Image (cartoon, helix red, strand yellow):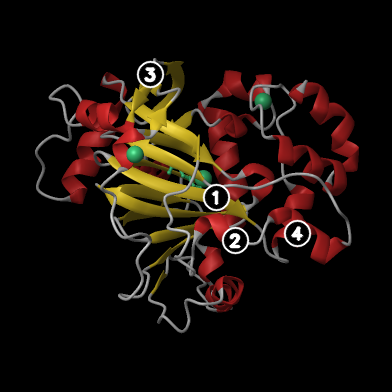
Amino acid sequence: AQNPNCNIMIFHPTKEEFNDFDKYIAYMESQGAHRAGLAKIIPPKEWKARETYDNISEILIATPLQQVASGRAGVFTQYHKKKKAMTVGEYRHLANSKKYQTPPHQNFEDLERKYWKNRIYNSPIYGADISGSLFDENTKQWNLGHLGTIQDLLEKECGVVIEGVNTPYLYFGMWKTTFAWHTEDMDLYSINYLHLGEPKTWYVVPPEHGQRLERLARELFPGSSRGCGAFLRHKVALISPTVLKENGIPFNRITQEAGEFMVTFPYGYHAGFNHGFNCAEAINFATPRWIDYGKMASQCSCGEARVTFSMDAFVRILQPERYDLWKRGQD
Ligand SMILES: O=C(O)CNC(=O)C(=O)O
Ligand SMILES: [Mg+2]
Ligand code: NI
Ligand SMILES: [Zn+2]
């Protein structure tokens, strides 16, 4: 088997290899990339997402979220406090303010250390889950707004027609803005392009050891666990790499920089943080290989996780037994 230590692999497609998205995902998985739970894709030097980002200040962040932490440095939950709307311009200015800017540091490793030591003592504001794309419509390759849809994948593989659409989301980040330990909705893939700004650091557990993570999480957040058997779906728990080492949880880390794609694979748990003001775009996608992961995906039936319109149909078709109890959580 390829990639038996489950390392994060980095790919450098040629522009010829960058034409067929589905094919290159399949290629990466033939080299074992999926075993890590995450891969890096460096686009070919010829490729451009768009001409410039000169005009993006006028994008509105309707609901910025202040990420308030509770707990110890390496084991904490965060809750999202809703703030007043602001433009990307206002957000970027806020991200560069003395209160919120990235501190002095030698390298990513020094900054990682400061993040984990000082994360809980601060409340950065995130512009997350904003519907839209910054890909130019004339960008034909790896345009996240022009991928085949999950519904069409489901229909090609299983013969069933369902409602739903699937569109990209933008994420405006600043120093310390954090994404908690999670898999994608329905354990789908995700693809994330870092359009501009400072880096994003990612941690990931191999899908074949996801249950080990889940078990640690139940021990670390014992109340949350009683409340909901898929409480990582709530996207609030943080666990540091030190804590993961101490408890024997296999994992890897990598930093994504501007102009790079990351792909998460079905049931690859991930978490991470932003180094400073940036903007990423992301979307879930599926392959034939996803269908069984979707069949087996854990669901939140405590009602905290509150998920998209399009997820109804996935659960309804792939998880008909779960569908009576799950939709009562969604309503
Ligand atoms: O970019 C973020 O903050 C979170 N991104 C992801 O979890 C993803 O693309 O799967
Ligand atoms: Mg604008
Ligand atoms: Ni994700
Ligand atoms: Zn729940």
Which mark is first along the chain, 2 or 1? 2
Q: Quadrant of the N terminus?
A: bottom right
The numbered disc on residue 283 is: 1
Amino acid on which the number 4 mark rests in the picture: Asp
Which mark is first along the chain, 4 or 2? 2
Is label 4 in a helix, a strand or a loop? helix
Residue 183, image x and y in percent?
Answer: 58, 45
To which residue does mark 4 refer? 152
Query: Which residue is situated farthest in the bottom direction here?
Result: 16
Residue 272, image x and y in percent?
Answer: 39, 42
Where on the picture, by quarter, is residue 121? top left
Q: Whole-Å distance between the Cαs marked 2 and 3?
A: 35 Å
Which mark is first along the chain, 1 or 3? 3
Residue 155, image x and y in percent?
Answer: 82, 60
Mark 1 or mark 2, which is nearer to you? 2
To which residue does mark 3 refer? 68
